[PDB]
Image 1: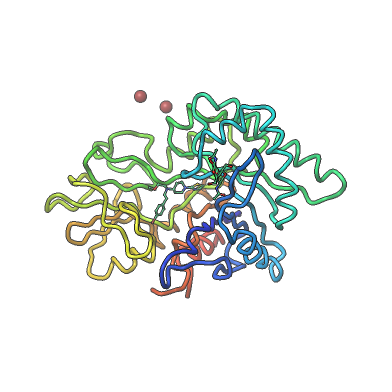
Image 2: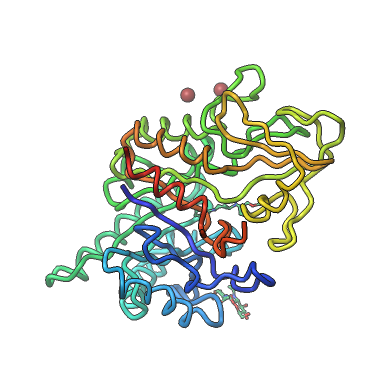
Length: 358
Ligand SMILES: *[C@@H]1O[C@H](CO)[C@@H](O[C@@H]2O[C@H](CO)[C@@H](O)[C@H](O)[C@H]2NC(C)=O)[C@H](O)[C@H]1NC(C)=O
Ligand SMILES: COCCN(CCc1ccc(Br)cc1)C1CCN(c2nccs2)CC1
Ligand SMILES: [Br-]
Ligand SMILES: [Br-]
């Protein structure tokens, strides 16, 4: 089984024990660690943070004692230009420039592959996205024909049915990618103005859910139905939770809200909490496991957060193995309890143990 784990460079700037650098990562925890994110500048792949070369080194050092560990560099994100990615994929000139720039950059900085995290191609760039993936794979094939270990090509794909329908040609890009990480979190499941778990495993109670596609099971089944081999499918599991400010004494799935939850001390973003922030939050809170959805939420005062814990990620790993998928993907290592402030990496270690069947 694959255990694909993301590291985010901006996590270095977090205060106190939130500060996360690649040397805090257990070199044996994951089979693949993906560094997020790299830039596209002048139609070339390039660094993003000022100390990216150094952090690259800290990350790829981890393979010294661990030769099986593979690393990829992720390009894209949600604070990208996105028009830039479309320009590179649509403009043939920019496309050849980017594709040619990638293998030497990766070899120079010690990465074993590239990860595409374009969010999102859209209706206009579905075909350009397919072309980009095909020609990227072709250049990787050419670069290593003289008996070199071939560069890997992966892609993080949305788990949202609408985005999947408008953005991806699944059966075509699946034959070129080494694996597909399906982002089975950030689901916009709940009715508007209402609490909902952002990463439920199953639909759960039928009349308590606005639609059928806003759950992990549906997204995995759909991507399989569209022609993605199970052996190339890596199911994403979040080490973060989605939070809401309650508007009433109702604390269940479906309760009214006035907006996003209060930002955590370390990540400082309304509506989201890192898992260690959630561990701090759990002191004094009540945890209810959503019966049909197999994931927990925790409530305290006017605060509601749907998250994943050790039991729920064990359940999700059992799901992916029953489906015979390639493994699990984790977003993100720096959002797990990496310093063990509440052992270390509790959620990712739970995923890793659960991946070891029986
Ligand atoms: C990522 O790449 C983009 C594209 O080259 C950079 O955008 C330019 O940044 C310079 C410096 O601030 C500006 O003067 C230009 O006007 C920008 N051009 C465009 C088209 O956006 C961006 O700075 C890069 N980011 C990082 C962190 O390296
Ligand atoms: C409002 O946030 C929406 C963006 N979501 C969540 C970001 C977030 C997490 C924790 C905190 Br605390 C604050 C923000 C990301 C999640 C993972 N991501 C990818 N996974 C694989 C490749 S790209 C897609 C977008
Ligand atoms: Br419909
Ligand atoms: Br359907």
